[PDB]
Amino acid sequence: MVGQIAKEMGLRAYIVGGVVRDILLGKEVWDVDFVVEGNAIELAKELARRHGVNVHPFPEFGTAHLKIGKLKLEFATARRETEPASLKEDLIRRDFTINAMAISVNLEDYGTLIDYFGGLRDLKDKVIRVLHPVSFIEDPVRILRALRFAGRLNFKLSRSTEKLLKQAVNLGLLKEAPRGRLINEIKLALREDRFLEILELYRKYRVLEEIIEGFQWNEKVLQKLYALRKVVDWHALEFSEERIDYGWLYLLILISNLDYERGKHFLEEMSAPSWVRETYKFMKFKLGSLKEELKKAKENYEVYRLLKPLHTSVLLLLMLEEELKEKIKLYLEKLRKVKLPKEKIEELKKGKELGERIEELKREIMN
RNA sequence: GGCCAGGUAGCUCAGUUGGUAGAGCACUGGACUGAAAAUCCAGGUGUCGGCGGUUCGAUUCCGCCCCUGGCCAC
Ligand SMILES: Nc1ncnc2c1ncn2[C@@H]1O[C@H](COP(=O)(O)OP(=O)(O)OP(=O)(O)O)[C@@H](O)[C@H]1O
């Protein structure tokens, strides 16, 4: 219906950005980005009116947001910078060639993909390529983004883009960049399933040393990341109904050797979840003694008492130890699963004494 | 859209090793009164946001959503 309203208004609208990429990658998303030559606001208002839904105009930015069903629509006016601006000027201000393309929703040319910079070629060649040599200088945040994309799509940086990125990092532009944008970029990074690869790229180009103060790479941490990779794989395989956010675990492994002050500060900047902060504060201190207690474990009930109050993340961190692995697993798929019939429990009930008695019965069943 | 709080009676507010809930003023009834108020005895003062899951048992553990306020990414 967009092309029709655009025809009535005598305008030109286009699907633009990653939305196109995902479309070309076969990935269907509910968030669509539009670039409109002429006023996008009235277009969004009319489209919202015909479908009979609310509209959220933003005149100063020149963009408008409206929601139809599960579809989240954003209409943006064509702008050459971050006289009417052409679509090409609006695309050339973007980061990478794969994100620089567009698909015309105009009724006459409808279905046609508009690619000026050959982003389609780079898409088929699995290449992350910047539009201009000053790209990383303009927006240092992109230094992360590229890597992030290279993590997700499993693409490779072109020689040009790679050299330019390395030069950009060597100038320490990553420190001059706004803290919030970088932190948010890392937040977007850790949400990826391929995030580990993004960490490999972060290690390769050493951006984490720039962003995080006091952070240095070693082998133990990396091996811990791959072990955690295996644990995450298994847990997301069998226990998948119990899934939690995995990236934060890797993030904890990275900051494990860091000082508690810098760790708490970083987690504060990242706006980490409560269970993440708890797992970190537990890891930095009580984790060692916990392991030492798990080493002295003989009966299964002691293992129960030491494990059950803990979260799943802590257990996954306990699976990093080879000796504790099968123990944790045994606690998972067997130990904590059990029940009791009616008459028996009725005999058990005859305050806290009922609970203590139940515990005595459980440790009576286990051992 | 991300996060942090806040959600407790009509209103204003505390509450952690899960184990049988609270304050200050409105609410009902009776004693009291010509009527009313005060006051006394008392006692509602509540599925402690909503829906699932774990647990013998969840205001608490978790997950998904509702509401309000504040930091922002926009
Ligand atoms: N710092 C930047 N510089 C230039 N162009 C950018 C920048 N950030 C975003 N863009 C462009 O604007 C679009 C905004 O899309 P969005 O913010 O959703 O990111 P994305 O690439 O779609 O990934 P995701 O959907 O995971 O956020 C992107 O497709 C990108 O082409």
Image (tube, coloured by chain):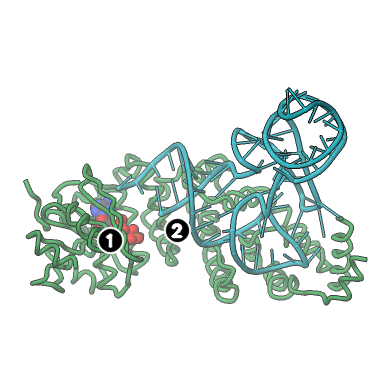
Chain colours: A green, B cyan
**A88 and A290: which one is in front?**
A88
Identify the residue at image location x=34%, y=54%: A144
**Position of residue A109 measured from the top left corner of the image (x, y, whole percent):** 9, 72
Q: In the rendered view, does A83 fall on the left or right side of A287?
A: left
As helix, strand or loop, the secondary structure at mark 1 comes to: loop
Quarter of the image where the C terminus of chain A is located: bottom right
Kindly identify the amino acid type of the residue bearing the numbered disc 1.
Gly
Query: Up-down: is A17 above or below A177?
Result: below
Which residue does the image show at 88% across and 71% down from the upper left? A346
The quadrant holding residue A189 is bottom left
Q: What is the crowding at mark 1: few (fewer than 14 residues within 10 Å), some, or many (at least 20)?
A: few
Q: Name the residue under label 2.
A: A190
Vertical relation: A334 (above or below) A67: below
**CB under 8 Å between discs 2 and 1:** no
Disc 1 target residue: A52
Percent x, y of residue A8: 9, 62
Residue depicted at 38% across the width and 44% down the height: A180
> Closest to the observer: A144 or B49?
B49
Label 1 CB-ligand 1 distance < 8 A: no
Q: Is residue A50 visible?
A: yes
Residue A121: percent from left, percent from top: 18, 71
